[PDB]
Amino acid sequence: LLSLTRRAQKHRLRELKIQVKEFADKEEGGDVKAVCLTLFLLALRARNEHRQADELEAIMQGRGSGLQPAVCLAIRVNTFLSCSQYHKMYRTVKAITGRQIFQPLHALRNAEKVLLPGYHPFEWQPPLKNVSSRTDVGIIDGLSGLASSVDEYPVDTIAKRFRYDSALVSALMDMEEDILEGMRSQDLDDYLNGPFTVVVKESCDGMGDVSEKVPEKAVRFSFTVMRITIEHGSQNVKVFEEPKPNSELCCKPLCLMLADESDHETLTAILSPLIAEREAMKSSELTLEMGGIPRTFKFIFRGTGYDEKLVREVEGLEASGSVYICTLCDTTRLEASQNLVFHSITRSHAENLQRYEVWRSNPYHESVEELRDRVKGVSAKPFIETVPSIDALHCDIGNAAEFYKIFQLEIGEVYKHPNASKEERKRWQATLDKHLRKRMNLKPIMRMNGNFARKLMTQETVDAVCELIPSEERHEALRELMDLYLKMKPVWRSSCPAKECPESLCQYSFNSQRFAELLSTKFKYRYEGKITNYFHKTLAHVPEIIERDGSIGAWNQSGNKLFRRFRKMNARQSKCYEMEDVLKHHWLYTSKYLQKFMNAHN
Amino acid sequence: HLLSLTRRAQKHRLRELKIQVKEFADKEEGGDVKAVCLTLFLLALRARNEHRQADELEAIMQGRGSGLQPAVCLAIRVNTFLSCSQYHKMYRTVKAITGRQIFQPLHALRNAEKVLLPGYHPFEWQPPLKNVSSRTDVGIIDGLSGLASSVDEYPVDTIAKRFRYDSALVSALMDMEEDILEGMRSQDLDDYLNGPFTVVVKESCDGMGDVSEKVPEKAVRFSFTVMRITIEHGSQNVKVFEEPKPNSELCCKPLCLMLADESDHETLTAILSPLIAEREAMKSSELTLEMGGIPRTFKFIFRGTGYDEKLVREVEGLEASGSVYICTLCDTTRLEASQNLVFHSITRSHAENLQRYEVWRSNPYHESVEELRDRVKGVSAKPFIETVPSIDALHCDIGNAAEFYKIFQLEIGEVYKHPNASKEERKRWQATLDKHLRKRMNLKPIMRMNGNFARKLMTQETVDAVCELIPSEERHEALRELMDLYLKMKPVWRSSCPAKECPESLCQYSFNSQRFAELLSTKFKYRYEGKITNYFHKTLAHVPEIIERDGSIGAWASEGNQSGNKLFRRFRKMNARQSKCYEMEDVLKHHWLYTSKYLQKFMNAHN
Amino acid sequence: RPPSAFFLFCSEYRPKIKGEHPGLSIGDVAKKLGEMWNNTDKQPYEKKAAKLKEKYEKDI
DNA sequence: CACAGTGATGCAAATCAAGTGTGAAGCCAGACAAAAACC
DNA sequence: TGGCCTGTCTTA
DNA sequence: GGTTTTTGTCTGGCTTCACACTTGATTTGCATCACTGTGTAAGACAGGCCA
DNA sequence: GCCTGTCTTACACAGTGATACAGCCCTTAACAAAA
DNA sequence: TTTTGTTAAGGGCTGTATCACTGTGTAAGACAGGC
Ligand SMILES: [Mn+2]
Ligand SMILES: [Mn+2]
Ligand SMILES: [Zn+2]
Ligand SMILES: [Zn+2]
């Protein structure tokens, strides 16, 4: 029967075909497919041919010798193949192996729809203020209806975005598998639906020059699901937390725009609807179906991803050269330099909105200098609530810069030479450079960086520099200073110091105070009314930041490269649709679902 | 639903049909329940239009294994511009998820590359080539060819990489092996036949403009294109291979890539002269090379047709294009060419040009510069490459249309009757013509000359259109005949083989161009200014001679290499080590592989 | 693929080992073959292996 | 400065290939009753 | 006519 | 309550793989190399307002 | 009756993701041609 | 007696041929310095 061709087998089996179709229509409502599938699987199992039966079951589940269109999508996206390229590979492999290993282009588009915002239905209770309840919304114009007539302000920018809620929905549905499995891993039940709390790191950076060749700048507003806890009784048990918070991979894009991060008018115009949406979500519950069961989520948004320049810009504060050097407190550069450590986090978004109104209203009729001291730098109206933090890098860098200056000044013995000239200090610096090259193999550089700081902040480096210091009494002081630095460093370098270094976390304030004291006694020569934002944050606010955020390390220079990559290779060369394609592509590229396939070899 | 329930449950719900099927199998098919259920399910799948799962089931039952040969993997990687890391991601993922190794690992692809690159097969030259090594394992070689680089010497500011020309000839022939054997078969000849094959190689060279990724960075490409292979089978030369798309970037095998300016004569000659030496050497020897187990012998014919005019002039010692000596085939001046429209012949040659450079250099009749220049016809520099300058079908059309357009404007202004006209009058004439073409012929106006304007304007319909703007009908008759002559000439320069497709057109071309020029000289006297373009001169003077020399025109066109620059930059960005010595040979190797016919066959497998 | 020299050797020597001990398991017969051939003379095996190797190489 | 990302590289570890006798794993048949949802 | 406080541009 | 289903129960004798062990020459897996171009931000540097 | 770079856009086409259209093997019964 | 072809009207997936669209390379011209 099998050596026969198609018309032959149709004929010689026509009788059984009629009998089988009759039985199928009469017993299963005409579902011939299910009847033949089960018949053949059961026959295979009956003949002890479990291998072929399992492979058939897998071909019906799409797991063997045919890639699921989602896996094709993961490959294509994750390898930056264009549709033309992808189709060439698809058609070629199919022609040469006869089998359709990769799926066609229409299958990949259909698999895209599921992974893009706007596909699953959801509810907000109570309905979000000023946000549409439509759930089938995906990519929408980033201008949010900004007027474009020739009379109005000139619009020089193209941007595309998601509605912030819909994107949260898609990101949760993307991680559904991790959420269920984490519930299992905490010895909890799959079907529980009690209020899940999602913590969300909110992030914003400009991406420099994006141009393909005039500079073309881009802003990326993005988010990261940081942690999802479930409430069991009255314990909040974590069901998920991101392993690599800072990775490009889990940084879910929310809006991409072709604009300058310092173009304030445009920035507020484009970002303000997103903030409006996030405000809306701050007081509502999200109902979303996972695994057949309706689940309920509530969110905590923490804008910790903003470098200092963008913090200052969105919170109404002055530019970085200001005297008000801290975005956490009201210190001045002079105050922070004289007052070494006793500073506390003071500022808040509301305090800044009121300080703006005070600037604006001048209620006590003061002069501009008196008003500026009254509002401690807030001269513009804030429009984003940030959680300004510190980067562990900048702690190391600020410390190392101070130690470098102390080393060169201890070699020159600056206390004995108060009127030392520029060239004498320069030769001091040259002496230290030369000796550090000979002893520690450190190429003197003129721009401070992480690797130089990492190699210089060692006890052995202090011994090396002491080899050039006459007084050993000052060897004592320099070595104790470096010891204190090495005690404080783990706290801000770890990713969870309350387990990895709890002794140091405790002793941090004692150590910081002793460090500042030793600077104020033995090292008075390096006081001149100047200190950096980074050094002030390291000595004044680190324990407070760990109390608030838990970690320093956990809370984008590839952003530029990745943006440009997508634009050049995966996007229509038309102003209308390039940004659509780039945003869609980046979103797909951050899906944990496709990433799982790409890691399958583990 | 049956699929909802367990195997015990589904067994229960289907027991009756199972018994009936066992009866049917024993009564009709010899008891093969397995085969009967398989065929039932396959045909049901085909009925629900789900051919994909049915074919996958068929292949898994046949057990036919799905494995791509490393060569096919390489053809896909090359032809889709995947870097090694990106290929490795796709490979590892497909292998992890299907558990089968459909794509091969990277080391297998490298190995498959070695076969397709110069330096792999062995060969011999009889007699051994003069001043060329007999080593056959040479691949990429430094393009400077041992050029001195010490600080005392001339400063070497360029990076170049190349193949040894015989070695590349070998690699390209081995690549075409399957096409050679199939062509012999298609000509009713024997696969094992070994009689002397002849290879007509087209040589080419061009600048690639800017290559910078962001200071300009220019590139030169030196290439060759196997145009046809014949075999002597009697006193007959049978055509067993002929390149189907000769201007494609796909068959333009890169010989030498160099980062240098095509106008930088010192570097140009330093880098190319070794190649020219190997090409010369090959002109006096026969290549023996094993194909399909049989040694074969190949004789080559190098024709340098791949040179645009600027490069022709530079390498053949002629003056720059603005000269009075406008033809690279003959000694005419622009004024002579304008006055004497049709009667010129192909008199220049590489030997004549070398000679005239010696004359220029030695000034043997002690002449003034103007007299000496006149004597040597503008060959003021020593040629260093023998070329075969030609014309492309495009410029014939372009020159004719530029002339007809100017004629149209002047005929609207009755200049045959009025000698003088202000700028405003001529501008209004041109506006009239442009409006009238936009209205009746749907011709957009254009501010610069171009091909398809010419194509669409050179129709008898446009002549009726413009005749609607001319009052005198004797001039209608004149225009209609001038266009008739145009149309009688066009086939010859457009067609692919004019000897076969339009033998009467080719036979009457010369007569027709004489009558064309006579019509212009009698009833169109006004359009004589002592000016004419090389395109128009070659079209009216040299087309039959070029056809007799080459067989055709449209196939030796300048059209294709504008993609080259794009190709180059792609390979430099995505498939190249980021180090100046290595990026170049990586682009070279990728460009070789991109041209291989073996791999292209895999990429056209569906047909 | 062509057999290793040791592999062709074992195919030829399976009858001697089998006739002398019939119920030796695969682990045991292979362990023996391996131990005695490892102790070994065996140059013709390598010759046959190289010949079969280059034959298979030719096979395209 | 760091670092991204290229094609090449180099060494460790699978892997292959043959012999076959096991053990493990799943399935068959037929009368029938639990634990379950349908009027 | 400056220091020099502020914002722009440069180089590692 | 009757009337419909799912899902077990008890055996063995079956069929179909995986493992077992060796040797050494291939093949894969994986981290690494050397290397520059490019983005970014640390840090020189130009500058004009008012005293 | 100048030479010869530099500059400027016209112009075509490349090559993107989306989209529209055509061609594909069938699906009913029956004869029946090759084997 | 066992395999395939075949008709006609007509219904879905799949393959490729465009869409529209703009950046971009090459080159057709214009132009101006040779103090
Ligand atoms: Mn930034
Ligand atoms: Mn050129
Ligand atoms: Zn502070
Ligand atoms: Zn001529």
Image (cartoon, coloured by chain):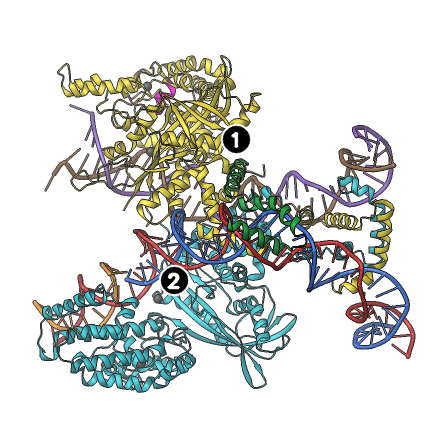
Chain colours: A cyan, B yellow, C green, D blue, E orange, F red, G purple, H brown
Q: Is residue A328 left or right of residue A456?
A: right
Does dot 1 land on a helix, a strand or a loop?
A: helix
Does dot 2 land on a helix, a strand or a loop?
A: loop
Please report the residue visible at 49 percent of the width from the left and 60 percent of the height from the top.
A589
- The image's mark for residue B178 is 1
Subunit of label 1 = B
Please report the residue visible at 38 percent of the width from the left and 62 percent of the height from the top.
A153
What is the three-letter code of the residue carrying label 1?
Glu
**Is residue B380 inside the magenta stretch?**
no
How far apart are labels 1 and 2 at the CA level?
66 Å
Q: How crowded is mark 1: few (under 14 residues within 10 Å), some or many (20 or more)?
A: some
Name the main secondary structure of what is drawn in magenta.
helix
Rendered location of residue A132, percent (x, y)? 55, 69
| The magenta segment | B530-540
Q: In this view, does E10 lie above or below A330?
A: above
- Quarter-of-image position of residue A455: bottom left
Please report the residue visible at 24 percent of the width from the left and 41 percent of the height from the top.
B157
Looking at the rendered image, the disc whose residue lies closer to the viewer, 1 or 2, is: 1
Rendered location of residue B598, percent (x, y)? 50, 36
Rendered location of residue B54, percent (x, y)? 70, 49
Q: Nearer the viewer, residue B439 or A552?
A: A552
Q: In this view, does C16 lie to the left or right of A443?
A: right
Q: In this view, does D35 lie above or below B231?
A: below
**Is residue B537 inside the magenta stretch?**
yes
Q: Nearer the viewer, residue B276 or B361?
A: B276
Using the rendered image of the protein, determine whether residue B411 is visible from the camera's viewpoint. Answer: no
Marks 1, 2 in one chain:
no
- The image's mark for residue A153 is 2
Find out if the beta carbon at label 1 lies less than 8 Å from the nearest ligand 2 atom: no
